[PDB]
Every structure is written in C-alpha cells, then in structure tokens.
Image 1 (cartoon, rainbow over the protein chains, first blue to last red):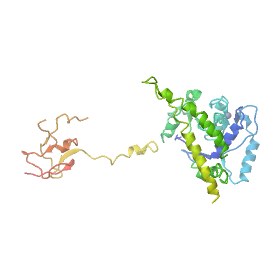
Image 2 (tube, chains in turn green, purple; image 1 turned 90 degrees about the horizontal axis):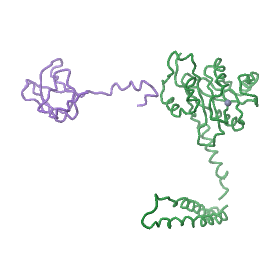
Image 3 (cartoon, rainbow over the protein chains, first blue to last red; image 1 turned 30 degrees about the vertical axis):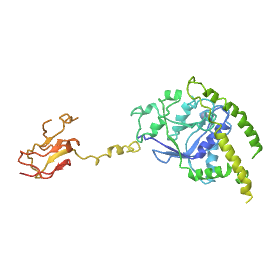
Image 4 (cartoon, chains in turn green, red; image 1 turned 90 degrees about the vertical axis):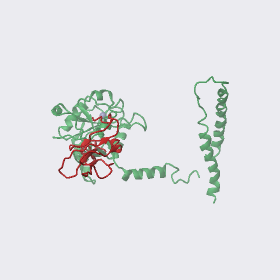
Amino acid sequence: AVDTAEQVYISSLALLKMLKHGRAGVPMEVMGLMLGEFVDDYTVRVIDVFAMPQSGTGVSVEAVDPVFQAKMLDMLKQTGRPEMVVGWYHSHPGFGCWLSGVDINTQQSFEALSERAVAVVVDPIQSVKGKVVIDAFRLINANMMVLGHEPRQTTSNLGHLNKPSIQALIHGLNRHYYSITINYRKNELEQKMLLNLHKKSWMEGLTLQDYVVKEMLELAKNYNKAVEEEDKMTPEQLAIKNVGKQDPKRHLEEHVDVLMTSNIVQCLAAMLDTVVFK
Amino acid sequence: TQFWFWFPLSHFLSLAYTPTCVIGLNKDLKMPKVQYKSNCKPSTFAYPTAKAKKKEKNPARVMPAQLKVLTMPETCRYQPFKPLSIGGIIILKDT
Ligand SMILES: [Zn+2]
C-alpha cells in the first residue's frame, strides 16, 4: 500500500552465474528463476541464481519445470539453506539489453504469484571489463496510476539510477517500467580472499619464479633503437625555423617509460643473482 | 546535510537560526521609545544617511554591517549602559 526505493544487496555468485550463463549462454536468449529472500520493503537480496537446462526452443512462461523447482529446493534443503525465490532472470546476450516481448508477459505472470519478481537483463558478450553490464527493472502497471509514479522516499539512489536513464526502447519504456537499484555487497568475506588469491597467484604463483631475463633484452634493445631513429626524426620537425607548426604534436613519450621500467627490470635482474645467491 | 537518504534531514534545520535584530529590554515587559542611529548609507535598509530608527518592540531587523557602525542615542529618556556591538536582545539604562 506504499512504495519505497528498493535495493538489491547481491551475492556476487548471482552475477557470476549470470556471466557463466551468458558467456556459455550462446546468444539465443534464455530464461531462468532468481532465488534470494525478501528482507524488507526498501531492500531485497539475491543470494542465489541457479541454472537451467538447455531450453533452446524459445523464451516462454512454460519453460519452467516445476519438478526441477521441487528437486532444486530439495537439494538446497539437503544442503544448508532452504531459501525462497525472489523472481526470475533471463539473458539478452546479443543486442543492447532491453525488454523482449515475452518478458512483457512473463514478468507480471511471475509477479502475480510472487511480490516483486524483478527482471535481470545481462550481456557479458558486450566487452571485457569497463562496462557495468547488468540491467534490472521493476514493472509498474496501469493499476498504479491511481497515485503518482514517484516513490522518491530515499532519493539519489533512483537519482543515480536515473543518472544513466539510457536505453532506446527502455527510456521509451519509462511507461510500464521504473528500474531498481543494484549495489554490490560489502563482499570482504569473499573480496578478502579474492584479493589474496588474486595477488598471491597472479604474480609467479609461489612468487619465486623469475627471481626471459636477457635475450628478451636483446630483442627489446633492438626495438629500442629501431624506433628511436624515428623518435629522433621529430626535433628536425621542431626546427621549423621561426614557427611553422600547429601545436607540439608530441612524441617524446612512450620511449621514456619503456626504457625506464624495462631497464629497471634489467638492473634488478642483475640484482637477482646477487640476491638469490646470498 | 544528506536529506535524500532521509527526508526529515531537510526538516532538521530548526535549532540553526538566531535573530539579527535589536531589542531594548530594560524591564521584561516594558516597551520604551529609543532612537539611535545606524551610520550606513540608507540603501543597507534593503529588506527582502543621517540616522536610523531601529527599536520599538517587534524589534527591527538588522544587518551585521549595521551592527559595527552603530552609535548610542543622546536625547532619549533611555540612554543605554553597555557599548553595543552584539545583536539580538541587549541592554538598556534610564538616564
Ligand atoms: Zn533473456
């Protein structure tokens, strides 16, 4: 009877199974169900996003196997946690992550039973790191135009969710849809160990490995001459006697730094034998 | 400060405001008639010279720049006691 700005404290395994489900999720779009717990009104959590069989027929509401639901929750009951579904996921791995024409039915088909049933759109087949590729929305309906479409209660969460506001047919779909807010949990219980294995492993394992050293320097110094002659083809172009050149057109760099850190590596490699030996 | 997070934070600025006015309270109910001067130009009277009239409790709204150019009166029944430099509610003495 009241509307507040929600929040999704994600288990990272949710997005991990979404990225596996999208990476291995061959760009034919696919459907599944989301499993969390409705904590309160202004927040929700997703603790789990489970897997589906290879339903390569079409995304529809019929694709949910209820015996798979029963056995899935049962195998969670013989495991430690018998949690509750919060909704449904799906995958849009080819195009620009916007609500398909079956989703516009199955969202309210699922939230006729559940409370919120927030959609989750994914596309890890965008590119590799710097996009934030996750997309979630909350179906507002024509029943709720009675009062205004403005929860607003905690603001600047929907204000920074409003800060992109950018997908073509979705900002067309301000109608029927207001998004939900997705932050990523204080995950130090896993971010701790991801950091620790990450840097205890992504440098030489046991880290006694490199401590290749010199014929790579031979090839690198021949690089560092073969490009240095075209490096020095620039101060002749700085002799414009008076002035005949629009702005510096600067090619000083990229051969300071390579020489700098590469021969830092070579001099500390010359250290390395006098280091390992005593 | 951060009133998006909680809309009552925008309400919470109650205790943050003190008056810039001038009050001739010699006796707690008494309303006397004093006329001192504010030596600013009379365009600091802009409320959205020779002298001023800032007395007669309501008190008169004052400017802090007006609070540093003031001068006590000489002809009233009530020529004050302390040299005045603080606003709000202040001193008065009969002479
Ligand atoms: Zn999908």
